[PDB]
Image 1 (cartoon, rainbow, N blue to C red):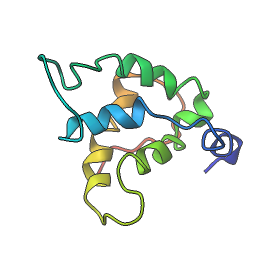
Image 2 (tube, rainbow, N blue to C red):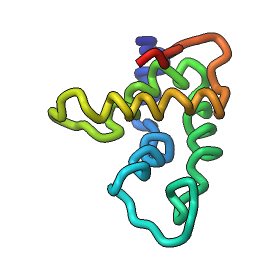
Image 3 (cartoon, helix red, strand yellow):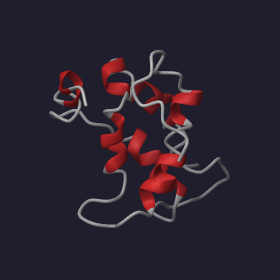
Image 4 (cartoon, rainbow, N blue to C red):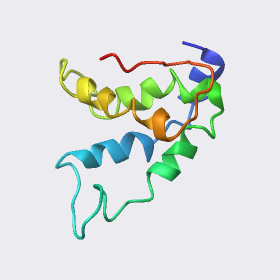
Length: 109
């Protein structure tokens, strides 16, 4: 909503490790050893948890909704990914406390 960040976050410094680790929750990524998911890329949470905060708190959200909106869809995939994509992107600010105030206090989805 706030362009002050929605204009600086999407300007040319969106997210990836944040909107990418979630992509590892599917078959959209390879696998080798054991791990919560991205065994070959475990360094994504502590990375995104920062790569999402590095843009300040005015970017932590709802701006993130962006990097999360393009976490999969990119033309028309109907209501499917966003559902879980969000149900798994809502636990990010839970273990990556990056929103003290409450920009995107979503979860009841």
